[PDB]
């Protein structure tokens, strides 16, 4: 199986023990590590953080004791916005310049391939997205033309049906991508007014669900139905949780909320908590497994958070294995307990290791 793990350039900036640098990554944990994110300047792929070059190096060194470990540079990302990509992918000159700039940049910097994270092609961008993926792949095949190990091409795709219908021609792009990472988390926005798990495996209680597609099973099944080979499908498993501030004494699923949860000490972003912040939260908290969704949530005082733990990610791995998918994608390594100092044992990367062990298991 594949175990594609994301590392974010901005985690280095986290306070104290939150600070994560590539050399803190276990070179043996994943089969692929994706560095996020690279920028696009003047239609060329470029660096983003002042010291990316230093960090790309730390990351790639990890390949020294581990020859078959693969690294990729992801371009795009949520904040990057879809505007820049569109303007590039629709203009024929911009597309060629961008495409042409990539192989040399990855070779110059030691990367094994490119990950596209265009979030998200508009309804008007569907075709352009397919064209971008097609030509980019041509260029890679053309670059390895002699005897090079061909560069890899992947794309992180939305797990949202609406988005999937307006943005992607799944059958076409699957022909050119080495693998697709479906982003199966971030399903329950706070705008809803109630508690809900952002990454449930299944729909669960029929009348306690908004719709039938804001869950992993549906996203997976749907991509399969749309023509994505199972062998090329990597399933997203989050290592962070989505939090809410409760509005009453009710603490179950669908409980009224007043807004996103209180910001975590290290990630400092309302509505979000890294697994290691969750572990701290769990002390004095009460945990509940959601019967129909196979995932837990925790509540304490006026706070509620839906996340994944050792038990739930193993179930998710069990699920992908049964569907015969290519493996799992993890967002994100720096959100897991990379220190191994916040949760139970002194084990580093508890969630990702659980995923790894499960993918190899029995
Ligand atoms: C069913 C359906 O369709 N539902 C919709 C749903 O999809 C939508 O929600 C969105 O979903 C997508 C998945 O499809 C999410 O994106 C993917 O998933 C992860 C996890 O969410 C994304 O991770 C976030 O990525 C952004 C950057 O792209 C991160 O932003 C960072 O924020 C920090 C702090 O705020 C910044 O740090 C600063 O850095 C500077 C220098 O770098 C430093 O000097 C500062 O000191 C430092 N601190 C501060 C505070 O300034 C950092 O710069 C910035 N990064 C960048 C490059 O801008 C954010 O923190 C990540 N969050 C998590 C969690 O890790 C990721 O982008 C993407 N993964 C991949 C592979 O592409 C998307 O995030 C999510 N949106 C939300 C709510 O976050 C929703 C909402 O639209 O709609 C539904 O309909
Ligand atoms: C990513 O690339 C863009 C250009 O494509 C960079 O440009 C932005 O920032 C510049 C410096 O402050 C501004 O002068 C530009 O106007 C602005 N974008 C435009 C319209 O060109 C951007 O800095 C790069 N991102 C980072 C942080 O490296």
Image (cartoon, grey):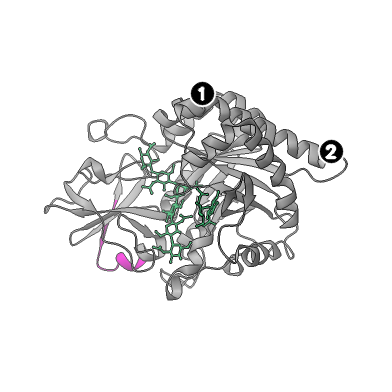
Q: Residue under circle 2?
A: 145
Is 286 magenta? The answer is yes
Magenta part of the protein: which range?
279-288
Does 221 sit left or right of 108 as displayed?
Answer: left
What is the number of the mark on residue 31? none
Mark 1: C-beta under 8 Å from nearest atom of ligand 1: no
Residue 262 place in picture, x, y as percent: 26, 61
Nearer to the camera, 321 or 139: 139
Q: Residue furthest bottom?
A: 16
Does 234 sit left or right of 255 as displayed?
Answer: right
Q: Residue under circle 1?
A: 225
The N terminus, quarter of image: top right
Given this view, does label 1 or label 2 mark the residue nearer the observer?
A: 2
Q: Note whether 64 is above or below 313 in the view shown.
A: below
Q: Measure how far apart labels 1 and 2 are at the Cα level.
A: 34 Å
Residue 35 in sight here? yes
Tell me if label 1 and label 2 are in contact, CB under 8 Å.
Answer: no
Does 215 sit left or right of 107 as displayed?
Answer: left
Structural crowding at the residue carrying mark 2, measured as other residues with C-alpha within 10 Å and reported as few (<14), some (14–19) or many (≥20): few
Residue 224 place in picture, x, y as percent: 53, 27
Q: What is the secondary structure assignment of the residue under circle 2?
A: loop
Nearer to the camera, 146 or 310: 146
Q: Residue furthest left?
A: 248
Q: What is the secondary structure assignment of the residue under circle 1?
A: helix
Tally the marks.
2
Write the residue at 51% across / 63% down.
Answer: 349
The earlier-in-sequence mark between 1 and 2 is 2
Q: Residue furthest right?
A: 146
Residue 362 in sight here? no
């Amino acid at each position: 199986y594949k175990l594609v793990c994301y590392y974010t350039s901005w985690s280095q900036y986290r306070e104290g023990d939150g600070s994560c640098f590539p050399d803190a990554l276990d070179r043996f944990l994943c089969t692929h590590i994706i560095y996020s994110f690279a920028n696009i300047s003047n239609d060329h792929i470029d660096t983003w953080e002042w010291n990316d070059v230093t960090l790309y190096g730390m990351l790639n060194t990890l390949k020294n004791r581990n020859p078959n470990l693969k690294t990729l540079l992801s371009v795009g990302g949520w904040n990057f916005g879809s505007q820049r990509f569109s303007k590039i992918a629709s203009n024929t000159q911009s597309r060629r310049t961008f495409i042409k700039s990539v192989p040399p940049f990855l070779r110059t910097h030691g990367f094994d391939g490119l990950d596209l994270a265009w979030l998200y092609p508009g309804r008007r961008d569907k075709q352009h997205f397919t064209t971008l993926i097609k030509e980019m792949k041509a260029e890679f095949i053309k670059e390895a033309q002699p005897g090079k190990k061909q560069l890899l091409l992947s794309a992180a795709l939305s797990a949202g049906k609406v988005t999937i219908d307006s943005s992607y021609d799944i059958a076409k792009i699957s022909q050119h991508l080495d693998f697709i990472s479906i982003m199966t988390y971030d399903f329950h926005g706070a705008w809803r007014g109630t508690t809900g798990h952002h990454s449930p495996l299944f729909r669960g209680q029929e009348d306690a669900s908004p719709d039938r597609f804001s869950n992993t099973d549906y996203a997976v099944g749907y991509m399969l139905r749309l023509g994505a080979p199972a062998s090329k499908l990597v399933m997203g498993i989050p290592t962070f949780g989505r939090s809410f501030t409760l509005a009453s004494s009710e603490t179950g699923v669908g409980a009224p909320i007043s807004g996103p949860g209180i910001p975590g000490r290290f990630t400092k972003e309302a509505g979000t908590l890294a697994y290691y912040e969750i572990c701290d939260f769990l002390r004095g908290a009460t945990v509940h497994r959601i019967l129909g969704q196979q995932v837990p949530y925790a509540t304490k005082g006026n706070q509620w958070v839906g996340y994944d733990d050792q038990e739930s990610v193993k179930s998710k791995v069990q699920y992908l294995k049964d569907r015969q998918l290519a493996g799992a994608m993890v967002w994100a390594l720096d959100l897991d307990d990379f220190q191994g100092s916040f949760c139970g044992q002194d084990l580093r990367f508890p969630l990702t290791n659980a995923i790894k062990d499960a993918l190899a298991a029995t």
